[PDB]
Structures are given as C-alpha cells and as structure tokens.
Image (cartoon, chains in turn purple, yellow):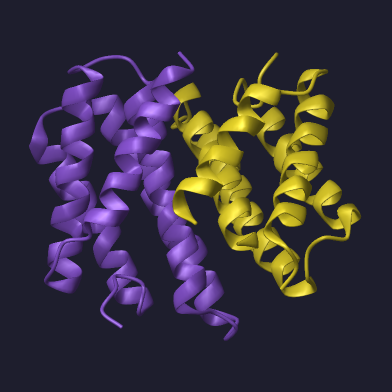
Length: 126
Length: 119
C-alpha cells in the first residue's frame, strides 16, 4: 500500500531524499558521499529499465531499494574517514527515516533496524 | 588484481561470471534471470563509463559489487528459499574463483546473513 516502491517516481524520490539527508548529517566524507551518489544513480537507472519492460512490480522496486540500502550500509561500515561507525550508523538510520517520511508520510522502523543490523554485520568483517 | 573491486575489468568479469553460473544452476526462472541480467548490465555499464570518465574508485566498485550481490539475492527472493540461496552462493563462489583464483566463503556467508535479515 503505502511504500516508497509503489512507483518509479516515489522510488527515485526515496533515493534522492536519502542522498540529500546523508549529506546534511555531516557524518560522511566527500568521497563517501560521492560513492553513495554513484550507487543511487546506478540503482535509479536499473529501476527505470525494469519499468519500461512492463514486467516491473512493487516487489522488484522493493528489491532494488533493499540493494540500495545494503550498499549504503557497506559504505558506512567499510570505508574509512569521517566519524565513528556508531555515528555513521545513526546518520544512515536518520537519513533512511527522512526518506521514508518524505515518500510515505511515515517511518519504517523495521526496515531501518534491519539496516542497523546489516551495518554491524558488515563492520564485524573488518 | 586480487579482488573483484580491484579494477573495472575484474568487476565486469565477476558480474559476467555470476550470471553465467546463475543460469547453469537451473534454480531461477527465466524472468528472474532476465531481471538479474538487466541489473547486471546496468551496473557494468555504469562502471565502464566511470573508468573512461576518470570517476571510478575502489570504494565505488566495492559498493557497486554489494549492490549487485544484494540485488541478485533479493531479486531471487516459486522454488524453496534454501535452494535459491544455495544457487546464489554457488554463483558467487564461481565468480570469486574466476576473478580472484579462489572462493570467498566469508563474503558468501555475509550474503546468506543479508538474505535472512530482510526475509
């Protein structure tokens, strides 16, 4: 029903809202933000192609959105520079929540807590 | 050199190796393989352009590799989940072997863990 992946426009809106908020947190280096932007742009491109094949779905956009967030988690956990992993984790979580609010009018604590766990998981292997 | 995100050619090789092995497992539907192929093609193209425009980096290749691996897993997520997950794992191992000369059980275990969290 009320998800960021109900359409390509809202899915784009989610990624763009996240990118804007990530930058405003100040928790990430310029290079880290550039890397996030690259992932976001690539995911949006994929979403656009699937939309055009007319075999797209909320589920497929949802999967690409999870891939986007998983990449964000990896950038936060792996790339060095800027603040601590704990600060980065809070920044990713807040930036995701902002994206959920701007596209759905509500938070998504289940999704965000999953990304929190994912960051910790990636952080272990370093 | 030694990892799939060491260079653009190795990152492409990883994605192409994965797609070929994914098809050979027989665990995925034609539509699933098509979507995987589209996402793979999109990422490779982005990387190829980045290399030539001098906007590439290790950070972007490693993150794009995670976007790919997480996409392949989630696109897959019909048949049983464990069978699909094992197919995703076999495809990852084959891709690591063909690009780095060895498997990467650590990476695969992370992907397994990633699948469990989202499910």
